[PDB]
Structures are given as structure tokens and as C-alpha cells.
Length: 50
Length: 50
Image: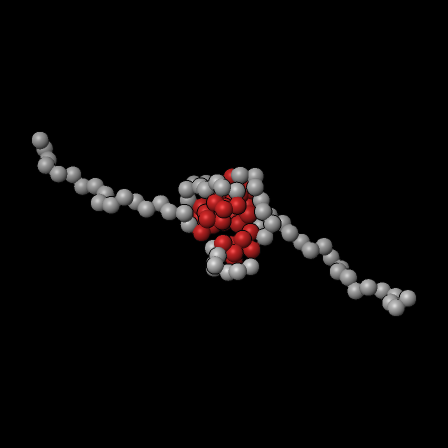
């Protein structure tokens, strides 16, 4: 072997239902991953070619 | 007649798809009326007896 250990994530990443996600969860029942990121890509700077 | 005119509204009470509804407009095609009311209900104090 060239190594005996590898670094990595220690705990599971927490992806939780946030608040605007909770609103669209109750109303229509369809939750996206990153709702604030969709807001930043749509209603803040839509012309920004990401 | 007890009155000759009635004091009524002068313009249409406007409502357009603003920022927070627009994400649900594009991703779902599900726009609600007064998204701010739903966010004030089921996010900030859902314990509030309506």
C-alpha cells in the first residue's frame, strides 16, 4: 500500500426542509433541493450565466 | 335617496407574481395568492390559533 488512511467526511451532511421549502411542502407537496439557490438564480440575478 | 354616491375604490387592487411566487411559477406551475400570508402562517408561529 501507498497509504494506510484516507480523509473523508466525519458526519452525514444535513439536508433539511427549510422554511420556504416547508411552505411549498405543505401547499403543493413538491420540495426542491436548494430553494434559496433557486431564488438567487431566478429572482436575484437571472442573467448571470452560471 | 338617503345617499347620492357611494365611496368605493378607485383602482384595481394589484397582484402580480412577485419574487417568492416566481420560483414555484417556473419549477411547478403552481402560483398561490399571498405567499407572504402562507409564510406568515405555517413558518412564523404555526401555533397561532387562526
